[PDB]
Structure formats: C-alpha cells, structure tokens
Length: 158
Ligand SMILES: Cc1nc(-c2cnccn2)sc1C(=O)c1cnc(N[C@H]2O[C@H](CO)[C@@H](O)[C@H](O)[C@@H]2O)s1
Ligand code: NI
Image (cartoon, rainbow, N blue to C red; front, side, top):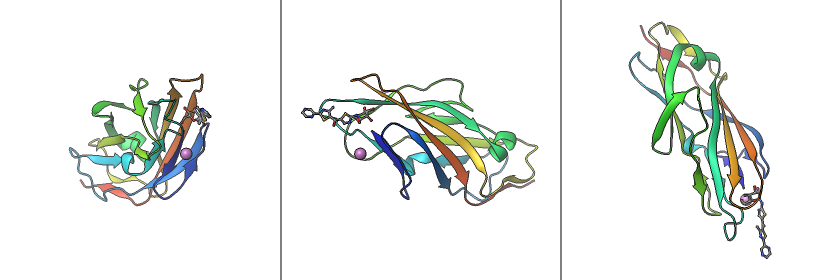
C-alpha cells in the first residue's frame, strides 16, 4: 500500500510525508464555500489484494495559516461531513485493488465575517491531513502525512 499525488509526489510503502500544492478559487464571499477536493490529487492502492484488504481512515486534520483564522468549515469524507479541524478519526474506506483510487477527502471552508484582505497567502500551508492505513492481514499501522499548500491567493470581498 502506497500513495501518490496527481503530479507524481509519492509516499512509499510504510508511510511518510509529502507536499501537495492545490489551486483555489480566487474569491470566496462570506456565506459561500471554498472547496478543496483532494480526491483529484491524492491516490492510493492495495499492493496485494489477492490476500489483503487495506483500510484507510482520515486520522486527523488540522488547519494552518490563513484557513486557521478566517475560515470555519467541515471535511467531507466518503459522503459524510465532519467538523474541520477534525475531532475524531473517520470511518474506514476499503482499498480494493491495485488500481489507483482517489482518497475521497474534500474540505469545505467558509470565511468568517471578519475575513478582510487576503485570507490565504499563496505558497502558505493551509492544512495537514493524516491518512492512516491499517489492513485485515497483519499488524501494520502507518500514517501518510499530507501537507496541503496553496498555489494562488483567495480574497473575501467586503
Ligand atoms: C501478502 C502477500 N502474499 C504473497 C504471496 C502469496 N502466495 C505466494 C507468494 N507470495 S506476496 C504478498 C505481498 O506481496 C505483499 C504485498 N504487500 C505487502 N505489504 C504491504 O502492502 C499491503 C497491501 O497493500 C499493506 O496492507 C501493508 O501495510 C504493506 O504496505 S505483503
Ligand atoms: Ni504499488
């Protein structure tokens, strides 16, 4: 079991960390959503499904810099939403195949009314999300730590 970003950053078997750079809508209005759909950028696969079945949770998610201070919101993980920053490990997702399969985590962030100026600086860390992979076969428990960075800039217009 390993994972890769869209543009080819790779976290190997056993876990590790990676940076993932994402494009954001340039304007979000107070009352509207800024979506971060990592399921278009983070992909995983079972490396021997013949015998093994891999289980994947979002162990933990945390907000940094801009999103940490001008935004509230949730994280949708497999059809269901949860508070973000996270308060609890999410349910398991089953990684079936040797075929690359999206990590289906997306953030929905709304700006607080005091969000004025540039809410998120470009090139800043906005989120860290810890992918935790166990299985049905041995005692393996590995964290795949993704550091989410912003490409462009987002402003919230007064
Ligand atoms: C499980 C297994 N049986 C093999 C076999 C069976 N019969 C005759 C010859 N050989 S080879 C064989 C194997 O190749 C393995 C392939 N990956 C293995 N472990 C890694 O991948 C698993 C599946 O994604 C993860 O759940 C685990 O955490 C770790 O990352 S063991
Ligand atoms: Ni592989």
